[PDB]
View 1 (cartoon, helix red, strand yellow):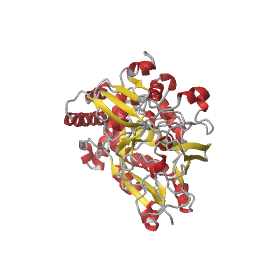
View 2 (cartoon, helix red, strand yellow; view 1 turned 180 degrees about the horizontal axis):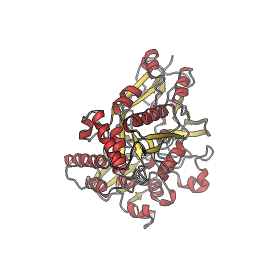
View 3 (spheres, one colour; view 1 turned 180 degrees about the vertical axis):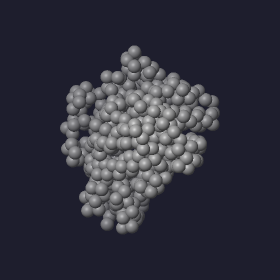
View 4 (cartoon, helix red, strand yellow; view 1 turned 90 degrees about the horizontal axis):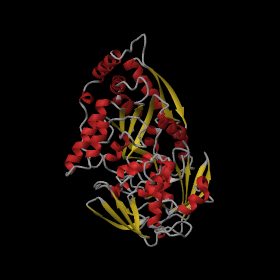
Amino acid sequence: ANVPTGVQLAEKQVLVRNNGSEPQSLDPHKIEGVPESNISRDLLEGLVINDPNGNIVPGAAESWDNKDFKVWTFNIRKDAKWSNGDPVTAQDFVYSWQRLADPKTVSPYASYLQYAHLTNIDDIITGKAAPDTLGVKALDDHTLEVTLSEPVPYLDKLLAHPLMSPVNKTVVEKFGEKWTQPQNFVGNGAYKLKDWIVNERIVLERSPTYWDNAKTVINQVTYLPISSEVTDVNRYRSGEIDMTYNNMPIELFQKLKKEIPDQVHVDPYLCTYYYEINNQKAPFTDARVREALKLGMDRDIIVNKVKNQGDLPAYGFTPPYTSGAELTPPEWFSWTQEKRNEVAKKLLAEAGYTKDNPLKFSLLYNTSDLHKKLAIAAASIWKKNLGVDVKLENQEWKTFLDTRHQGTYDVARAAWCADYNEPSSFLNMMLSNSSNNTTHYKSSVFDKLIEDTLKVKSEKERADLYQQAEIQLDKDSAIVPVFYYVSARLVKPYVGGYTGKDPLDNMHVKDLYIIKQ
């Protein structure tokens, strides 16, 4: 942390942060959500990390270089250590990435290595080749060489993702599934696992072995699993919580802005809220049905009138303010909602749907005040505009995600957040074989366009290919874009270090600090 000279630090450096929900796990290769990533970042550190403003800086690796962006060499920090005193080595990373890729691990982020384009990853994921054939090796215990199948200029940004953090082989093989337990957990981040009570809390304490410990200020941080943004806020206002999760309840937003203006932070956030259509489940396999729901949704109402928290109506998947994105909204985005509703009903009609036989389906969302109110608004808008009937259904975060991967849903509320500030971080999730693809959209046409992005010889050609990719997504109406996020959260006045300038909002508790009174 960087305490600005002048400000006095409180005697008790303790922090309580809400984290949306009970995490899926603390193992980096078993996670996929923001709640997960939040805790993962304090406990484990990858080759490189994001600073308070989103810039990529040295993590486990002190320096690195690349040859043609195809071969990357990282010089592992000589003082990087695990919480148990063992050295963090190049082999640790070789072991970790091989585990991530291994189908036996069933990681929701196995494809991340495909996004990175490590050599032989495709055969490993399918099970045709052994994980040890992965293009990553330790030249020596402190030199890691990464070989890609093609040049990837943004590899450095990509590597900051939790999922690319190392795990301790000894510990993992020793306790297996029980390695993330408080008594067994070993990490290399700024904090270590003190305690974990399912549905109640997770406590992290300062890790003395962390190579940058001298700058760490907060000695203990507690992550709560409160999914009710209302309870969360009211459990910020009563003083029990220092930083709310970045999901504000519609019931209390305006009141909060009026009562505690300077504590309400709303900043650009690279994430997109959309309704995910199961592309392989019947009636939604029909592009006309999908397109109708896409056109029938009224973004102006749900975004600027129901939520009204600063978000931007979305016309595609990739946020246009993503670095390197050069997008423009599709034709239909320009029409009037009346016009769009006209087209949508025509499509539903020629698709065999009528007043006598309307489209009826379920809308699934993860338990939450916010998503519930948005889902009710969405069900309402589609009914009035398309005459379809939507039955709402909610599930807890962990089950919600599982359900989506299993494809046991019709329509689900969803949100994808960038892992790195580049368009492919979004578009790659739509690739037909991506372990992250919960929409089940499979298009060889879309896959080719993204694959070509790395065969380009100019960034302009790249930006152009991403646009074509977005066009292809829209053409097939794979999803129903709703809005590009703003990160809205409450931060106590005495909590310093939060800048709100990191587009990815990849905060590290090691950069925070408690101001005196």
